[PDB]
Length: 71
Length: 96
Length: 48
Length: 70
Image (cartoon, rainbow over all chains, first blue to last red):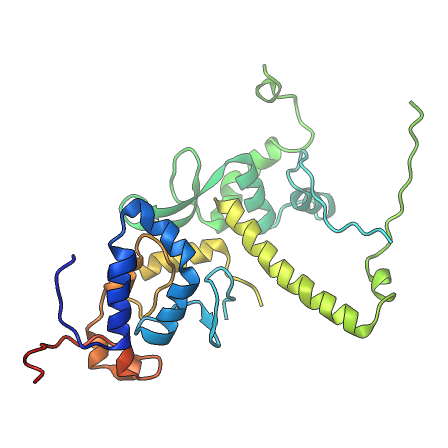
């Protein structure tokens, strides 16, 4: 909801702040294109520095839910 | 050397897959029947809230009610067969 | 209009005997990847 | 050796968005709901590092006071 929260400056929290300052603030019409553009960067940061990694990551290789198998 | 790398068709039994199933086996498998229902517009795909609960899968194109793959055959086999292949000329497909 | 025509289609596997082991293997790997991608595209496009 | 069917991708996303369920510990897609996926349920990882990729505190979110940290 955009309320301030003090948090320890963990790598995940710094990613949270960066996304707050570069992705989340943007308007709704502008959020989808920027997510598409920075998909690779966002996935890399989620996998490296955030508690919720990108799901479609198989043995470290960033992938997609449509590009990964059932196993 | 020339190789047929790909192929397809639009015919009285839908695509090449459905036509081949009807040609060889004389009937549609589950996959062939679902492809024919999708081709004929009997079943459409729905994903999201439907009657409150979230539904993902095939629905009836007209009634929008959920239809399971197992029931696709029991619900649309007769219509697919009646309105596929060699049949009485339908004026609605040739402008009255 | 007297349009006679004849084509002959041979089994695809007679082609693969004209190439090496390595070339066939790399070709097979590339068709496997392409088959997966094409399945993805076909089903997505079917539903949507 | 068979990529997910698009129907199963849609099902997977819907059941990720299921409300009677603990929010999933990952981002399944990047879309309009990416903020919801990214921010929701971000407090328990501080006390449950055993459920983290490398059990690394650097990945988790710990609320804390800058002045009280002295």
